[PDB]
Image (cartoon, rainbow, N blue to C red; front, side):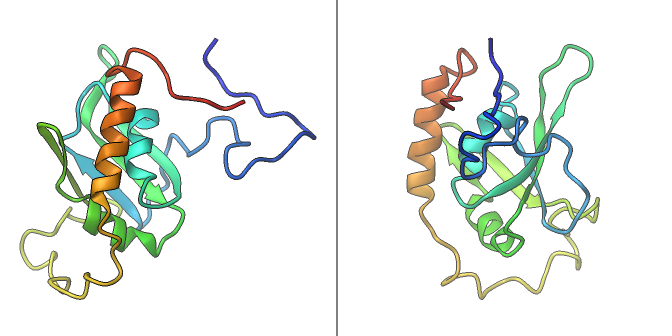
Amino acid sequence: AMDYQPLPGMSENPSVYVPGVVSTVVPDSAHKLFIGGLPNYLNDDQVKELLTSFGPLKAFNLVKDSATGLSKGYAFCEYVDINVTDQAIAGLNGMQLGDKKLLVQRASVGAKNAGSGGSGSSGSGGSGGGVNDAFKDALQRARQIAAKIGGDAGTSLNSN
């Protein structure tokens, strides 16, 4: 048994009462983050602990292979805190966990992803001050939870 059922009338919880928490399909918006270069053995739930560390997440849609059923190495997610997007992406881009680092860029409804030529400018500064640079705490958290799960060999859904 590996599922979450809330108790109707007994605690509404902070933000876990919803079974299937964080939408598995992320509605196309400008606060949609694209994470590329992530381990194929990490899916939405497992990557949540890395991404949600910076702010509250609303939806998480990993690119999953339809052939055999594993992560394709990329994911799309959106912060409910639309403001946190700019800070989180600035802190999470280049997130280096062990020997693998993720490329976190903006999907923006299939805009261009980081621009890379005109469409990726006007942001070369004014990031220091608002970004909480605790990627150390996020790293430790993520890597220890990844180890806790055993690299997709268990669960960390402690919802009781």
